Image (cartoon, coloured by chain):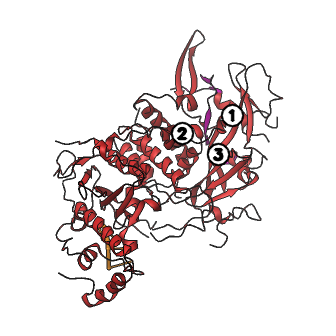
Amino acid sequence: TSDIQTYTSINKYEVPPAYSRLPLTSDNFDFTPFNNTEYSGLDPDVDNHYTNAIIQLYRFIPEMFNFVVGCLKDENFETTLLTDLGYLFDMMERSHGKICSSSNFQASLKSLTDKREPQEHLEEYLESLCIESIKRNMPQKFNRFLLSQLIKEEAQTVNHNITLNQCFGLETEIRTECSCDHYDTTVKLLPSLSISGINKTVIKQLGQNILPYIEYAMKNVTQKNSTQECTVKNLPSVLSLELSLLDTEFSNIRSSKNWLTSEFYGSIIKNKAVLRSTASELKGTSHIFKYELNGYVAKITDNNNETRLVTYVKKYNPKENCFKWLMFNDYLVVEITEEEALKMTYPWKTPEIIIYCDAEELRKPFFSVDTYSINYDILFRDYFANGREYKLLTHDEAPKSGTLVAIDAAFVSLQSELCEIIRPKRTALARISIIRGEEGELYGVPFVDDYVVNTNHIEDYLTRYSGILPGDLDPEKSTKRLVRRNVVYRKVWLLMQLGCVFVGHGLNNDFKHININVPRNQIRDTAIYFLQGKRYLSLRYLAYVLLGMNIQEGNHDSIEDAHTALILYKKYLHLKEKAIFEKVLNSVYEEGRAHNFKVP
RNA sequence: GGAA
């Protein structure tokens, strides 16, 4: 970590190590030399880590954040992309700097884009997932696709919302003229601008800033024969810009000092829109709209000709009136100054996506889902997409802050290592089972035993270790009970929300594949308790040398593994109440040598 | 060497 958080160099050509390529986390990885703030980063071990820069861009828009997280009160399993983004957004705030992964988001996105002119985005975005790491015009093409899919799903949710259109909606009126006696208009609500192919130059020094480029994209006359004039008469809350220029324009844009205007005032006077720096040069006839830059995504062309995206973010501080600027690499997060955040002089920096937010609207605080009324009906309700020894929970069993539950999950392997670029990427969740941990009549009996549906191709079920047979096909199911993934995730998320305490064997690597982060006070992992330096003790072994159980033979079963993980934690509490915490534990060292940690 |  030789100055890995250094984001500034003595010259303009040497890229700082803060923008360098980060080593992949392969699970025994220290993140303290990469993030000193309470703002989380993203695991680059995904199919396409260029989107990670864009999710971090939207996480810091109060309107974009509070809505997507707000949709978590109601249960909207049909909108796969909006709710998985809400799980991801809520995960980043709860981690307070801890690492986060967007595997569920990219998996829901890859399955959504694989549902194949309404298809122009699918063949383009789906091709980048499989995969000069990133090409040109790809981040902007995903920025258009992400907002177009969220708003399309923003309607199909419960209690239909139009919040994203009141923030991103551009009333784009575009008219085409056949002849001088005929003119036809079309009205389309666009979520983002497109500063693409700007082959028009006027007197510039009146160089200049970005403001004329936004004015051109808001009202321009185009000539294309298969004349045309498109103009927007709306100044929405957040302005999502997608720069698509030429290298001759990008070379001449890094010379104009302070081109990326931090804050500006704009209003609609004529049929077009006017944008000037301060309110003094504004006419003042209409009502003024102050816009501040909320963040942007830049492309970094490394000295080794490596391409990767980073995210710049400004977040307001309600305590004292200032602005904390942040630079988001994959998992490298640094609190940088604004002067360094706006400087475009570096040739290895190319702005890709820029967002502008309303001044008074950016100061709005970020509201978590905990301040809302959440609907926990999925726990007590049986949701089966099919046609069972557990018993569903009753309202007398209302989980509160401190309820004990035993959880054990089973996964499958979709893809191999594919190294030599070295990144084991694919692993899919197949089954979880949560057990009642509270003592009483309904003790040790499960309440949800769901199999996660999966339509993707499976490489190996790992049946000897997962107990999963090829009955995971939705129609042709061996059908323990096949339930979707967005529903079974909500059961785990709500228990963590309420404050339930999870017990089990190896919960850290289970939640990683589940793609959720549960705090320490809610995790009781028997592997960390019955720990002897390295060489984590086997669950079949602890259930033999500490208990009289000959288990984990034939095919594994999460119901059996979670039940024995619950009594093992109960036997741990027995040995802890009396001062025998070491005698039984130090003796299992020596007894394991004579048996070589295996016995029939 | 565990979970898979």
Output the letter for the chain in orange: B
Rendered position, A163 above or below A270: below
- Is there one chain holding both mark 1 and mark 3? yes
Q: Say whether residue A182 is left or right of residue A525.
A: right
Q: Going from the N terminus, do you reach mark 2 or mark 1 first?
A: 2
Q: What shade does chain A have? A: red
Q: What stretch is highlighted in magenta?
A: A219-248
Residue placed most toward the observer, A362 or A396: A396
Label 1: chain?
A
Of label 2 and label 3, which has the lower sequence position?
A: 2
Instruction: Point out residue A458 in the picture as x, y percentages from the top left corner.
Output: 27, 57
Q: What residue is drawn where x is 51% and y is 50%? A: A51
Per the model, the C-alpha gap separating discs 2 and 1 is 16 Å
The answer for which chain carries disc 3 is: A
Say which amino acid is labelled 1.
Answer: Glu
Which disc is residue A66 wearing? 2
Residue A198 in sight in this render: no
Look at mark 3 in the image and give the residue it sits on: A295
